[PDB]
Length: 230
Image 1 (cartoon, rainbow, N blue to C red):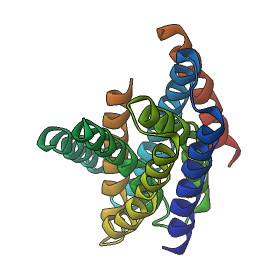
Image 2: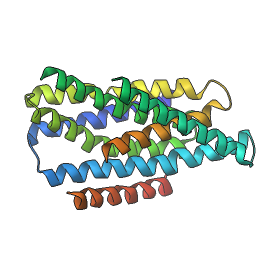
Image 3: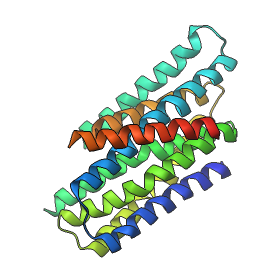
Image 4: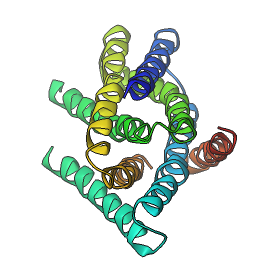
């Protein structure tokens, strides 16, 4: 649980840094924003593929067996996660700003949850790549969040403040992750699949298409590297 708390803290720190760069930038081009959001989306997609689905398939493979029951566990967890983020996306001037904040929070939930779930078995080979990747994507997402809050009408100070506070969803999401992943033996792969599907829904809601494609591939590739090296 401690390593997951440190991971969520790294998420909030990265989001805070990216948010603080907006104090100096104030505004950015559409190509830069699309490239950053595509980069983060690719990092999150490949993070769902290689850092959540597959390690959960291995864990359920050692808990249940090599048969299709493990893939059934992970897959059902994934469907439950997609259904969860779908329900959250359905059931939910200054009001528009609040809606933007809510969208940011629901975006940042499955990533903290991904950290906490990934640090359930204590394996650094599972948690470290996903956590580091979530910080690396969290910097441009903090920047884009602050700049987007400034473009809608908030001063750059208020926007950076709301962005830094939006980074607090990663630690809370991590506590939820270790909460749902440490109940029983099957809770770990089910939670891996759940976080994977939740993040796939979020990035599906987050995906000048050429530039965004350059970022998407650029950090899908980055991400495969992080999973291979760590």
